Amino acid sequence: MKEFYLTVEQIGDSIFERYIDSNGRERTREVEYKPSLFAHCPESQATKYFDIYGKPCTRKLFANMRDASQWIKRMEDIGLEALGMDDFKLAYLSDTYNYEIKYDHTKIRVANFDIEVTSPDGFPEPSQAKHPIDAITHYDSIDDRFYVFDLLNSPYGNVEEWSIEIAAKLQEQGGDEVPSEIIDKIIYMPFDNEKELLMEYLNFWQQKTPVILTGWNVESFAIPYVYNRIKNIFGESTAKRLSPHRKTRVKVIENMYGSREIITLFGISVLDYIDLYKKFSFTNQPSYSLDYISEFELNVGKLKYDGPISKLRESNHQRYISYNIIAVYRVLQIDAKRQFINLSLDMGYYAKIQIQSVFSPIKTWDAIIFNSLKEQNKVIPQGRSHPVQPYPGAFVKEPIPNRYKYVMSFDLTSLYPSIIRQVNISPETIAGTFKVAPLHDYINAVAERPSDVYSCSPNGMMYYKDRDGVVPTEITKVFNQRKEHKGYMLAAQRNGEIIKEALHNPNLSVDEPLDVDYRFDFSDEIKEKIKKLSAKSLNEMLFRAQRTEVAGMTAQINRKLLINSLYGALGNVWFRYYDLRNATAITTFGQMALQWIERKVNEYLNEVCGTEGEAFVLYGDTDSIYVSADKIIDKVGESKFRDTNHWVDFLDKFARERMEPAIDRGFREMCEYMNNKQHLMFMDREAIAGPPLGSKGIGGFWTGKKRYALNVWDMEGTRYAEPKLKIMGLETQKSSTPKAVQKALKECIRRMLQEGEESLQEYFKEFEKEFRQLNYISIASVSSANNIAKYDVGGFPGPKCPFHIRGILTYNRAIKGNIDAPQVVEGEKVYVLPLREGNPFGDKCIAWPSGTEITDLIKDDVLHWMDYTVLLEKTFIKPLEGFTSAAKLDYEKKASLFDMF
DNA sequence: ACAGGTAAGCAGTCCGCG
DNA sequence: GCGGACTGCTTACC
Ligand SMILES: Cc1cn([C@H]2C[C@H](O)[C@@H](COP(=O)(O)OP(=O)(O)OP(=O)(O)O)O2)c(=O)[nH]c1=O
Ligand SMILES: [Ca+2]
Ligand SMILES: [Ca+2]
Ligand SMILES: [Ca+2]
Ligand SMILES: [Ca+2]
């Protein structure tokens, strides 16, 4: 089979590669890569290498990478450009693998692990590595086994071996409840002492050397600690065994009152799962502990136990080890669902970069663009330095705060990416410029046509319509990929709504779920069978459908992230092809396009409907417009409408039959105006919102820019079984507003849109009345803790000290001394609560690490001095007042005027 | 260093106000 | 004895 790399590193004048050969065996080699750079030369001297702009270049082979590095320096010490790929690692791959890489993941060794360290002291700082490692669970994807390393003897207590039979029993039977599906894949290994533990671990690591190393927070804790622990004991010569090439690099970076350590192991690709989740999950969590995340993604338990984790191993060792095995497993479950590793490999092998580089859009695209240029024998430009500069972006229409019964939305596809393709924007397709007229002239189709021969943009740039352009081309490949995966996703969504509509006929029968591929729209034969299935079989299918959707989502939203990131890279000084002229061409064209079609859409509707000068487009943001469909329902009036689904199907057809075509002709015209390479401004219908038939609900409302809510019935072709709320920017969508309030505010909104003002007040009085009995954790607000020290001023708030920071300082003060209470980590999330006058803490609020309960020491005080009144006003009432106010409505009734009656 | 701009809402301060 | 006019900090929408 076609070969493919595993990892690659540059060490001195050599390149170290681990790869899979034609036979599927993992090999390693050390190459004295002879790099090759370029320099401009006289037009006469002819060759095959030309820079992206069409200039001749002479190629220079170098004895070794070191000589090529010194040549780039000498070249700058002179003032001449030094073209070519300066990152010799990438050049090496590009050379070694000149073909679309087809890899086999079953050959890639993905390791997953977690360790435990008892510490009565406090949190075992990896830099110090003072306490012993008493447990290690390491899962190997090739062997598909959990290798468990237990330390039975330690200065913190000796314990009896772990029992796998006990781990398997249910909690309720005094067991640990370790999943059945992995009990057989566990290899338990007890040890008399730490040295033998650590020593046996390293030999294991030698035999099963990880290619991809993942885990939860593994990069900032596990790895560092196991490195420094092995260092402080056997010496840095042994510790370096963790690297297959015996080479490590330790970067420091210490805070104002803390020491953090960054270890890099050459020959291994570390993908901390928390970093993968932060970048690809598209979520913003109140806490990032595995428990919180595990519950959010899998709906599993809280992994409970009694006492501090510091005393867990000593009092219930059986559970301690079982909990360590389960934690490692939970990450596997989350990944089996989100599939971030697969995504990483896909992106990695597509661009020919180190796998750990998928975190860098700039690196990713540099390699993609590079490889694409190599094929046409072109030479890439040299990276230059630039000063940062602000530049304009998208346009956002100021909405009129109010309610909106029926609303319909429209939106363009991969906007910026499409704009790049339509105008043919790229570092080498620049033709020139043109005197520009105020932006509103082009919108109003009044300004003179910029060019008759070139592709143009309202910002004054012109691009060749004839040529190709590596960016436009390379950006189209990834875009087509997204197209596909988005297809499978939306299908899984639709198939999913069917199963829900079917959960209304739960047939009293014993079954087994159908065997279908949820990536495709269910066929009639299937749609036929499902109607007869049981609530049991239907649910498993719903579950499988949703897991298919999530998998699709991951695949699609992240390819979208990538292409949108190429646009951003154009606006970043570190990008080899940085250029504000191109970035601005994109955003400016966007501002024009959005408003251009606003003018248009407002015409065709004022025309058709009949009225004149009536604003149908009530809002818009970057590439979307929300059109009011009241008059479109008025010209027919609530009449020939049997049930809600009636007019929803009505509007669906109106947009799909009339509105859209109009829009297509509106953008086709603009493409002509700007004389662009090709028309790709495709704007289709999005959401259809409004209240249920004959309801007291307002259907929707806006309060300001980026702040609105709508009761949607159909979204991009999916007809929900139950109306789904679409809220944007309101408190309900923010991680900082307490969970109880998000849930409560969302119910108020739901009642406010689906039902009338009566249901809202009814629920408002109810909530206000019960608010006091909610758990403290669910009514606490959340916030990140940045620059704590900065406003320290010796344990007290400083100048302009932030509420959450303040609340932290009061915390460290209430636990000051007894080093055992969890310390708030600089840069993490924290729960925050307001304290009434007279509290023993000496302040109006207190803060503590999120995803946790406050230390049992101060917990009862804070519970007693909680200012429920401020919490209700600030987090609930104030924002509620915002929604109802803008929507012309009241939550707490009003002066009946008929009072005394 | 390591995709980008737009915009809202909360507090903290400072300053005008019989 | 605050109101609002800025400013710093968060976090969401594109
Ligand atoms: C979400 C997002 C958008 N944008 C820009 C580029 C986008 O094309 C534009 C509009 O964003 P979106 O409408 O969110 O997305 P999209 O147009 O790219 O694609 P689609 O709706 O088909 O999924 O805003 C970014 O630069 N970065 C981002 O992270
Ligand atoms: Ca743990
Ligand atoms: Ca879009
Ligand atoms: Ca769409
Ligand atoms: Ca959009």
Image (cartoon, coloured by chain):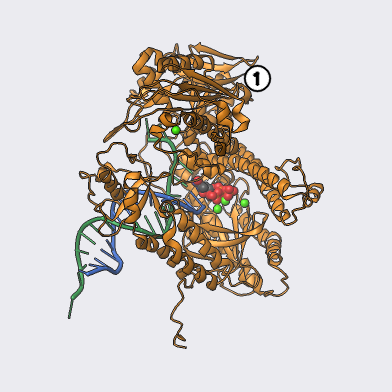
Chain colours: A orange, B green, C blue
* Residue at left offset 46%, top offset 16%: A202
Q: Amino acid at mark 1?
A: Lys
Q: Which residue appears farthest toward the front when viewing the image? A: A173
Q: Nearer the viewer, residue A405 or A388?
A: A405
Residue A724: quarter of image: bottom right
* Residue at left offset 36%, top offset 63%: A869
Q: Nearer the viewer, residue A548 or A190?
A: A190
Relative to A20, is A327 on the left or the right? left
Spot occupied by residue A742 in the image (x, y as percentages of width and height): 48, 57
Q: Residues within 10 Å of mark 1 (few under 14, many from 20)?
A: some
Residue A293 sits above or below residue A451 on the image: above
Residue A376: quarter of image: top right
Q: Is residue A177 visible?
A: yes
Relative to A187, is A84 on the left or the right? left
List the residue tagged with mark 1.
Answer: A2
Residue A623: quarter of image: bottom right
> Chain for mark 1?
A
Spot occupied by residue A494 in the image (x, y as percentages of width and height): 69, 50
Q: Nearer the viewer, residue A717 or A304?
A: A304
Circle 1: element type = loop
Residue A244 sits above or below residue A616 on the image: above
Spot occupied by residue A372 in the image (x, y as percentages of width and height): 57, 29
Mark 1 CB near ligand 1 (8 Å cut): no
Q: Is residue A415 visible?
A: no
Quadrant of the frame with the N terminus of chain A: top right
Spot occupied by residue A801 in the image (x, y as percentages of width and height): 26, 50
Q: Nearer the viewer, residue A328 or A358?
A: A328
Relative to A575, is A696 on the left or the right? right
Query: Number of labelled discs?
Result: 1
